[PDB]
Image (spheres, rainbow, N blue to C red):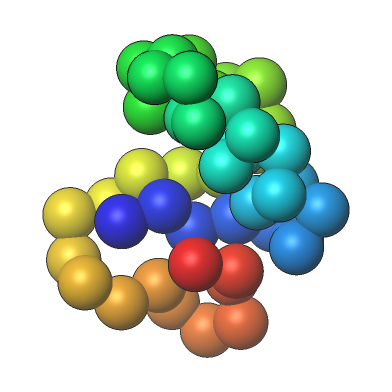
Length: 46
């Protein structure tokens, strides 16, 4: 599950992922974090 600082960061993450780019790379590009649980904490953008 990808949990992002903001909707802008998550939009950038999703754009990175669209052509297949590995999740960890898109995470570092955006500031989004990856957690195994189904639910992001607090008010992070899923």
